[PDB]
Length: 245
Ligand SMILES: C[S@@+](CC[C@H](N)C(=O)[O-])C[C@H]1O[C@@H](n2cnc3c(N)ncnc32)[C@H](O)[C@@H]1O
Image 1: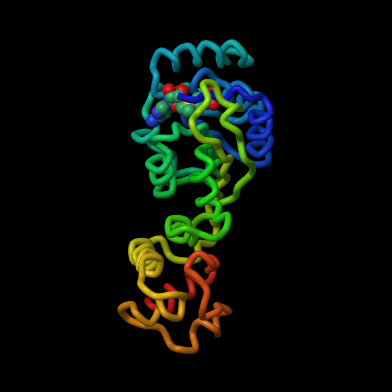
Image 2 (image 1 turned 120 degrees about the vertical axis):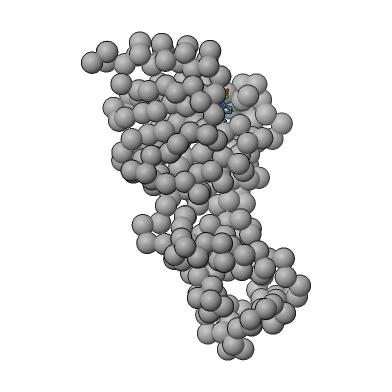
C-alpha cells in the first residue's frame, strides 16, 4: 500500500475538501495521513480502513486529537462492501492503485455523494478528466458527473513509492443530469458503440451504426465531420442519445 507522505499533497486535498459542505467519508484511511487533517475541518467524518489492526490504531489517534468523548467514526471495512448513505456527503481517498476502477465504478453507481476527491494513478486520472480528449468511460458517465484534474502527484510523494506517478481527481455529481438515470444502460451502450465503431471520423462512424442519424445532424450540432469520438462534449453525447433514442 502507498501511504501519502507528502504534506503539501495533504494540504492541497484538505484545501479542496474545505470548499465543500456536509459530512465526509474517507476511503483507505490508513494511519490517518488525511484523516487527522480532515477531522480539524470540524465536520462529521467517517474513516474507512480494511486493515482492522490499523483501523483500531487510527481510532485511538483520531480520539486523542478529537475534542473528547462528548466524533469521527473509524470503520474497519472493505469500501467495496460499505453502504454509502443516500443523504448528501463528500468522498475523499488515496486509492489502492489495483482497486481504482472497481472503487470508481462502486462510487459512480452509488448514492448521496456530491463531490469525490481521489488520489489514483496519473494515467487513469488523466483519462477520467478527459485530458487530450475523452475516453469511452468518461463519456459514459458525463450525463451525471463532471471530472477535474486538480494536480499531478509524483510517486516520490508516497511511502513506499508506487511504480507510476499519481493524479488528484475531483468528481462532482450534476444537480441536473443531462440524461435520465433510467436510460443509463442504453446511453452507455451507445457511447460504447460510437467509440468502438468502424469508420474514420464521426460522419463515417454514425453512418455504419444501427438506427442512423439525419445527414444534417453532425454539422447542426457543431461537430466537424472529421472529428473523433474523444472530441465530443457532454452536451453533444446527450444530444446524440436523444436523437438515436
Ligand atoms: C493506498 S492507501 C492510503 C492510506 C492513507 N489514507 C494515506 O493516504 O496514507 C489505501 C488504504 O486503504 C486500505 N485498503 C485497501 N483496500 C481497502 C478497501 N477496499 N476499503 C478500505 N480500505 C482499503 C489499505 O490498508 C490502505 O491503508
